Amino acid sequence: AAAQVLSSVESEIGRTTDPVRMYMREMGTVELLTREGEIDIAKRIEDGINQVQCSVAEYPEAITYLLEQYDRVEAEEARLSDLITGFVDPNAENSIDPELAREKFAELRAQYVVTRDTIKAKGRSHATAQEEILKLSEVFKQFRLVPKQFDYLVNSMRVMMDRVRTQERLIMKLCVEQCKMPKKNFITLFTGNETSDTWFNAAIAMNKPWSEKLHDVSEEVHRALQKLQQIEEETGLTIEQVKDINRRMSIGEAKARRAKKEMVEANLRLVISIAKKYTRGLQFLDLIQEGN
Amino acid sequence: MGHIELASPTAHIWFLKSLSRIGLLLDMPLRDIERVLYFESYVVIEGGMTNLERQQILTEEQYLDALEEFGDEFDAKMGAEAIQALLKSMDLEQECEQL
Amino acid sequence: VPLDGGRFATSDLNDLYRRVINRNNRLKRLLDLAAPDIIVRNEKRMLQEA
Amino acid sequence: ETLRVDPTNDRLSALVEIYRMMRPGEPPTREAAESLFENLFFSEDRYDLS
């Protein structure tokens, strides 16, 4: 409980105006980890990292976005651009060679072509279709890409999630807030069909005098529906799947941020110790920020 | 002439140390404002419940207590942003007719 | 302005403006770096001090 | 009367008050206070009367 004396010192400070001493007091609350904490934090970071890998693996177009760039640079008789470094580069537990890239892409094309028909069979929830999609995900997981392309890969997921969530919020922004749509039945009816106007006209079938005046807003409440359906068609993914992916990737990245935040301040003492030897060219406190 | 856009709002020094011109305007002690500017104590810009009140200084522990007790119902923060929000929330004519 | 002996001399206002702009762009980088809030508070404090 | 005004009751309290006087704001410890007190007037390098 090192924070209890914080109240007994701050309420009894001399109100020192020196930034350095108050900053080093602020960073003095935390302790130093050794021989168990650092490995724990590394594991807590890597589990989040592979959770993000799983989140981006379930995206059906992720494999296509990985493969189409290398396919484009294949017809160039070689891949001289830096994106060849951003190839699959499988993890093992050096320059990219054709005997590696093409060998890894053979099973990628195989899964790309064999995971299409199985989904159509016995619906999306087909057991063999789901296990084949998971097999494609696993064969995607055997890679190790570069952070550069991975950044835009996750940014595409972020922007598509933002677009779909804004479209979903627009339903409330247009009618629920104005016409007072009761969310108690709204949430139940929305998750039922989400593809047609079954619940939309089921609301009209009920008494619902507020909903009876929906024709004037039909061409502005159904455009959101059309946008949602178009997004689902171009993505090939249902609302529940993408929502689950976003929900788990958010907590994974939050855990990763928490772990790295827990780890950073455990070496602020190292930073300030190493900053002392470099002073007086610029300052003492700016060097602290650069070290951080 | 030229200008530099400051990422975070910052406080003018003449209207802070000269005796206060913002201490009277906010009717707050100078020490409390100095503590707020140094990122040491929270300030409640507005509180929905009657437990808290506007312009009440806050230490971190009871600030976390308020967070767990209320959360988004009350509004409190630090820095020169807090002072700027305080100046924003003030209505001059009501104080003019009241005092 | 240059001096006759090949040196230079300038007002300390230049030093103050350099310091403020340097830590201003440093805070600009730190804001989108999503660093822990302690370092952001420290950078804001030093921006105010500058 | 000086004893009457004195709030300290032992060496640790006196050293704590001395540390608070010399280095305001910085929390004192069990070892820093007497070290600073010794270096104030009892270290050859940091004090001299000739």
Image: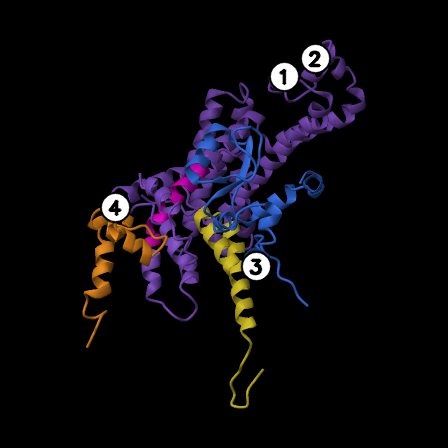
Q: Which mark is residue B18?
A: 3
Q: Which chain letter matches label 3?
A: B
Marks 3 and 1 close (CB-CB < 8 Å): no
- What colour do you see for chain A? purple
Q: Residues within 10 Å of mark 2 (few under 14, many from 20)?
A: few
Residue stretch rendered in magenta on the structure: A252-269
Q: Is residue D47 above or below residue A205?
A: below
- What colour do you see for chain C? yellow
Closer to viewer: mark 1 or mark 4: 4
The reply to whether residue A49 is in sight is no
Along the horizontal axis of the image, is A190 left or right of A7? right
Q: Position of residue A113 (x, y in %)?
A: 52, 33
Which residue is disc 2 drawn over? A202
Marks 2 and 1 close (CB-CB < 8 Å): yes
- Viewer-proximal residue among A35 and A110: A35
* Dot 1 amino acid type: Leu
- What colour do you see for chain D? orange
Q: Which mark is residue A189?
A: 1
